[PDB]
Image (cartoon, coloured by chain):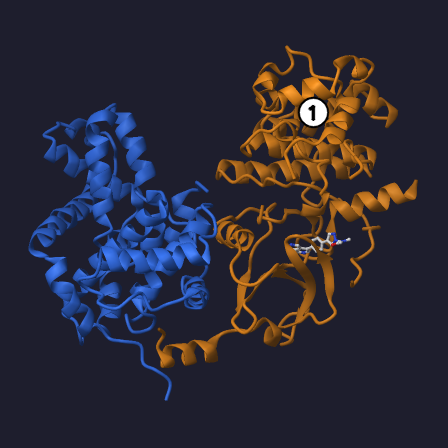
């Protein structure tokens, strides 16, 4: 699907207010600091990226899975459903929505086991504990708690349209595309329309590559104060990236994270 | 795995299809999609009929996924509206809720051919099918399986005579474009247009234009029936026919000479549709063998056929009494 964003469920229900988002986060902020909570969000973004790469899924599928994961925890506590179970469930659902297909029971469980064992052993000393019955249960909860909103718009399609319109596809697109991937280390996908994220990423790419695009950006007629807000977040994410050592910090942060309560 | 209090809260608050609707023994439809029930609310807040679609199999299949994803976004008077989704946690069945459509083209056509369709109704039906598919096509959504059984028509009530395109989850190849039968790998906007052409011909004659007796894309008997109606395409008519994966099979199994006295004019004339009518000229533009030479939905809507008397109406029945019987309980 490629519908009008202004009539989409993404815009009408999943473009949230930063303050309403901070208010819902308070429930988990009793155990984790604000800093540890964003670190945990980056970690699971990287877990979803590693899961998708193993399964050889297109960036569109990984981005859809990441947005599902974030939308779920924007409304619910980290203790509701284990994020270790939610991450491969989000990949499983996104692969179906994005017409890639049903990942087999064997392929999904082996992908989650292998990825956590190979690429995330520093944070998980024990093997992936879930089986297919856990994913199928989690899937039903995920679909329900997203109000069956499956179509997700990403900054990749408008970014490609902007860069092509500039006539700078060879030079700017590889860097701007990489910045869009990095954007998933933040909450931007929950706060701003994708075209706005794409423009800010293209802006940061122009600044890094030292290309004058002032006139092209000036002829757009978009809320530049909103593009500037996104730019500030992008610049902040690289400072966060520099100071964050995922491999040395995550076992402790995961241990502080609230765990699902068992039946009495 | 999951928090106890979280599960218990959701379980207490979750609306169950069996608590909200009475549908036991109210099955009206069956197929690949699943099952369809004509239900009534258990709480007397409404007396209107509702359609409950129990999806085939357990969990979220690709079909169930496509229907939920798209219908959650799509908003058009000629595309069926999804009102609610029920996720039955006990048996893992998915239920989709819509307003009940008393009629469909499969039952309407069947009623008329059993007699052996008013021309104003035919025109209004086609205009609403094209309006609905144009909206889908503008949103880059391809139906991939249009047929009379999927073109629903609303009965008595606030939407009387309104067409609703159903089945967004996508044995008989009567509505399948010739390029699909020759191995075209992808579905296109043109494939949906061919299907609309088939439906239009059937609305004008009460007969499926490419009716054929009963897993690879190549279907010989179906192609033979297309050629018996349309004639064998000349090289000039469909230049890229040589690029089709089954072109060599087509050359091996057929000879263009067999279909020399075959044409859509000859076929339509046997069923009393005039070759100089605006209806025929539009039908011929929809049923073009070469997909790149097939008219678009927007161009079809602009056809002078819709400007000729009578104009298409929002109620396809145009305030006249519906002769079609109500759907029977299976
Ligand atoms: C094997 N057999 C002979 C049959 O199944 C006979 N049959 C039954 C149908 C049928 C078609 C559409 C609906 C329906 C109504 N109202 C809203 C709907 C919303 C979504 N989907 C379907 C809806 C119900 C029944 C067609 N043919």
Residue occupying image coordinates x 37% and y 81%: B5
Is residue B208 visible in the rendered image? The answer is yes
Q: Nearer the viewer, residue B75 or A75?
A: A75
Q: Which quarter of the figure has residue A249?
A: bottom left
Is residue A29 visible in the rendered image? The answer is no
Q: Considering only vertical position in the picture, is B256 above or below B21?
A: above
Give ligand 1's quarter of the image: bottom right
Q: In which quarter of the image is the C terminus of chain A?
A: bottom left
The residue where tag 1 is placed is: B282
User: The chain coloured blue carries which letter?
Assistant: A
Chain B, which colour?
A: orange
Q: Nearer the viewer, residue B84 or A63?
A: A63
Q: Considering only vertical position in the picture, is B107 above or below B7?
A: above
- Measuring from the top left, give residue A129's x and y in whole percent: 33, 69
Q: Left of A15 or right of it: where is B121?
A: right
- Measuring from the top left, give residue B160's x and y in whole percent: 70, 52
Helix, strand or loop for disc 1: helix
Mark 1 sits near ligand 1, with its Cβ under 8 Å away: no
Q: Nearer the viewer, residue B204 or B241?
A: B241
Q: Nearer the viewer, residue B312 or A134?
A: A134
- Measuring from the top left, give residue A232's x and y in whole percent: 13, 48
Number of labels in the image equals 1
């Amino acid at each position: 699907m490629a519908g009008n964003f202004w009539q989409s469920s993404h815009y009408l229900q999943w473009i949230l207010d930063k303050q309403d988002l901070l208010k819902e986060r308070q429930k988990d902020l009793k155990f984790l600091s604000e800093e540890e909570y964003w670190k945990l969000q980056i970690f699971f973004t990287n877990v979803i990226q590693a899961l998708g790469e193993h399964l050889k899924l297109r960036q569109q599928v990984i981005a859809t899975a990441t947005v599902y994961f974030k939308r779920f925890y924007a409304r619910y506590s980290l203790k509701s459903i284990d994020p270790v179970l939610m991450a491969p469930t989000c990949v499983f659902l996104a692969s179906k929505v994005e017409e890639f297909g049903v990942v087999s029971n064997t392929r999904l469980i082996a992908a989650a086991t292998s990825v956590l064992k190979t690429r995330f052993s520093y944070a998980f000393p024990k093997e992936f504990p879930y089986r297919m019955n856990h994913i199928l249960e989690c899937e039903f909860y995920l679909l329900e708690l997203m109000d069956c909103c499956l179509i997700v718009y990403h900054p990749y399609r408008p970014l490609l349209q902007y860069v092509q319109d500039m006539g700078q596809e060879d030079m700017l697109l590889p860097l701007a595309w990489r910045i869009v991937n990095d954007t998933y280390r933040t909450d931007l996908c929950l706060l701003y329309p994708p075209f706005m994220i794409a423009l800010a990423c293209l802006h940061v790419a122009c600044v890094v590559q030292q290309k004058d695009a002032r006139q092209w950006f000036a002829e757009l007629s978009v809320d530049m104060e909103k593009i500037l807000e996104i730019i500030r977040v992008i610049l902040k994410l690289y400072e966060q990236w520099k100071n964050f050592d995922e491999r040395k910090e995550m076992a402790t942060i995961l241990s502080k994270m609230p765990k699902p309560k068992p039946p009495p | 795995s999951m928090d106890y209090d979280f599960k218990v809260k959701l379980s207490s608050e979750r609306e169950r299809v069996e608590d909200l609707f009475e549908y036991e023994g109210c099955k009206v439809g069956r197929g690949t999609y699943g099952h369809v029930y004509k239900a009534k609310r258990k709480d007397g807040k409404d007396d209107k009929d509702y359609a409950l679609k129990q999806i085939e199999g357990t969990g979220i299949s690709m079909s169930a996924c496509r229907e939920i994803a798209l219908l959650r976004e799509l908003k058009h008077p000629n595309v069926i509206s999804l009102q609610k989704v029920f996720l039955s946690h006990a048996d893992r069945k998915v239920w989709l809720l819509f307003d009940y459509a008393e009629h469909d083209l499969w039952h309407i056509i069947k009623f008329h051919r059993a007699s052996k369709l008013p021309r104003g109704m035919v025109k209004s039906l086609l205009y609403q099918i094209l309006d609905g598919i144009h909206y889908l096509h503008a949103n880059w959504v391809l139906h991939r399986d249009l047929k009379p059984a999927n073109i629903l028509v609303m009965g008595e009530g606030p939407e009387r005579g309104r067409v609703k395109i159903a089945d967004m989850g996508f044995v008989t190849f009567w509505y399948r474009a010739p390029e699909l039968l020759l191995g075209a790998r992808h579905y296109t906007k043109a494939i949906d247009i061919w299907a609309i052409g088939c439906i239009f011909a059937e609305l004008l004659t009460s007969e499926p234009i490419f009716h054929c007796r009963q897993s690879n894309p190549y279907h010989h008997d179906q192609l033979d029936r297309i050629f018996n109606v349309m004639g064998f395409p000349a090289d000039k008519d469909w230049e890229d026919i040589k690029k089709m994966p089954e072109h060599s099979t087509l050359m091996k199994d057929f000879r263009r000479n067999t279909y020399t006295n075959c044409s859509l004019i000859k076929y339509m004339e046997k069923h009393k549709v005039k070759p100089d009518s605006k209806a025929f000229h539009l039908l011929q533009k929809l049923l073009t063998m070469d997909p790149i030479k097939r008219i678009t939905s927007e161009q079809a809507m602009q056809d002078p056929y819709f400007l000729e008397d009578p104009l298409p109406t929002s109620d396809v029945f145009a305030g006249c009494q519906i002769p079609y019987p109500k759907r029977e309980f299976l």
